[PDB]
Image: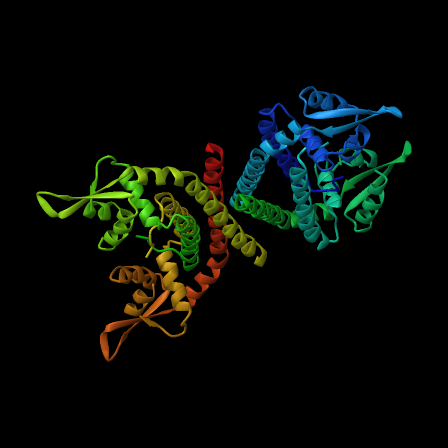
Length: 135
Length: 135
Length: 135
Length: 135
């Protein structure tokens, strides 16, 4: 968790979050995804072809991840397997089409990280210019 | 709380926090303060000459704020008043020397916010240059 | 021409030039061009399919532009036409292959301008951090 | 002199000059100076208590430097000495009041260089954001 910052540094940290979040939402909206869905698909790529238990996905990223995964399952992007010896546990793995989607997203996401860094630096420079010029 | 970011945006948000936190710690260390002590003194200035209940200070910023305030009381920077009708409640107000300390800190803190913004923008530009040049 | 700057602003202006120049040289070297050759080809595109007199090219950008254009002519990127009534005058126009080369250069050059702006802003922020921290 | 840049890099170099020049003009106007007068006073400080020939001042920075120096002489900031053996040569040295003026200008000029660097980096980041977002 975030320990005490001055109010001004704390508002700047939130502005950093808000700017980054908005740029990701705009790029992920084009693929009908959220960043949490991208983060699930990336996590499943790190163990592909093996699956991961729904609870372990939530722990590495909980009840909102089942609806999230339902959307990914309906799109054929992930495959669910109920553990035959423990029917409450659902393991989820990436499919070929989830791998393809992540390969198609590599360039848009890298550009999205470049736009984040650019806008963050401009926002910070606007505040720096303001502080230098009130002094 | 901070909703899902990509891992990369999440690490950048933590780098923003770490950089800002370190610059404040270095300037506040010179006055033998923490940022949470500065934040308490600023909060008490907004109601000066009135005091604020220890619980309301914690709520606006809890058991760690009493040791924090003890240090400020020992330095003569704040004045405690136990409520005569409710002895468990301790109201804390700024003193003249706490007001003076905040006036002496206005310039160092503004420079500290300028150094934060500068370093944040450079750190972000280093990552942007790296991403543009791997592509 | 550049009127009086402080020595420090003058050295910074030269650092701006040196950084921009080096990034262009590296991208144009890959197509076996110089920036002055790119600038000639762009100038000839603005009047294509008409040609421009060698002297007017030099004026809009003089004896070093004939060797420069010789290289472009040998590569089939420009076409020379000696004026039949005035044999000293050589009009130069872009060819289809010079147009194609400029279309292939649009993306690399835009990225080159993005890397220039990025590096310029980082170099300036390094000097700003240095000045704020000597004070 | 500045060798071939792309048109876009050349306009950016001029924007760098224009921004830096305007910030200096605004700070130097407050002391009723130009940057060329500041540059003369700094040059005379490097040889103080010795003077420098008017022609050597012009060479290190020519007929416009005599009016420039006249203003500095009228303000008691420099002292002229006509060479007794060569009456055409006028050596100019800093006075105590020219040294004092340069000591009073150290902080405003350093802040002026910080505002230049800040504004340059913001201007460049605005253009970088624009280029990344047209792509």
